[PDB]
Image (spheres, coloured by chain):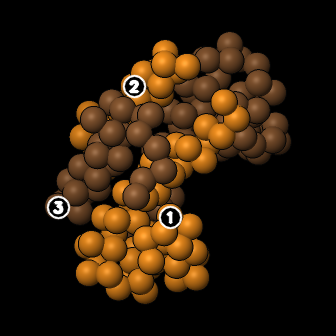
Chain colours: A brown, B orange
Amino acid sequence: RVNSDVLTVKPLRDSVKQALKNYFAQDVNDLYELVLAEVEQPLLDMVMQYTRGNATRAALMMGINRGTLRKKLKKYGMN
Amino acid sequence: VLTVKPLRDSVKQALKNYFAQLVNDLYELVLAEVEQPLLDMVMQYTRGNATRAALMMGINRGTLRKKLKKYGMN
């Protein structure tokens, strides 16, 4: 049913659901971007700490190329 | 807007726990754990109406149905 259960905070998906439930409880036209930004930022931050700042190693671990990683970091002013 | 307090703090903690347990698919791995529940919640909110769900998410209907298919939710 679900891809993996290695991300736990108690799956991370449950935290996403609760956040959305509380979000809906309080019109929208950018919910995907809203969520994507909220998840990419901490992901990039944690991956860069794990690879001690090595951008190539972070891209490899993420499964994306260096240019894509640079673009994302840039987007969040993490460059 | 997304809190549990902000959602990003839960993402960060989950990644800390995961790394301590240790890869070349971390992005898709995380995206799958976040997209599936988002798709579940929005489809639930709109009672399974793809047009309304896509409009709320800011993506076209074609992209929504592709994601749903990707995760075998269709």
Q: Is residue B36 above or below residue B67?
A: above
At label 2, the amino acid type is Gln
Q: Chain of mark 2?
A: B
The residue beneath circle 1 is B71
Specify few, some or many for label 3: CA neighbours under 10 Å numbering under 14, 14-19, or 20 or more. few
- Residue B55 x, y percent position in the rendering: 44, 79
Q: Can the viewer see residue B68?
A: yes
Left or right: residue B52 versus residue B23 is: left
The residue beneath circle 3 is A25
Q: Secondary structure at mark 2?
A: helix
Tell me which corner region of the image, top left, top right, bottom left or bottom right, holds residue A44: top right
Residue drawn at x 20%, y 53% as measured from the top left = A22
Which image quadrant: the C terminus of chain A? top right
**How far separated are the C-alphas under marks 2 and 3?**
25 Å
Same subunit: marks 2 and 1: yes
Residue drawn at x 42%, y 21% as measured from the top left = B17
Q: Is residue A74 above or below residue B13?
A: below
Q: Chain of mark 3?
A: A
At label 3, the amino acid type is Ala
Tell me which corner region of the image, top left, top right, bottom left or bottom right, holds residue B39: bottom left
| Numbered circle sitting on residue B13 | 2
| Numbered circle sitting on residue A7 | none
**How far separated are the C-alphas under marks 2 and 1?**
24 Å
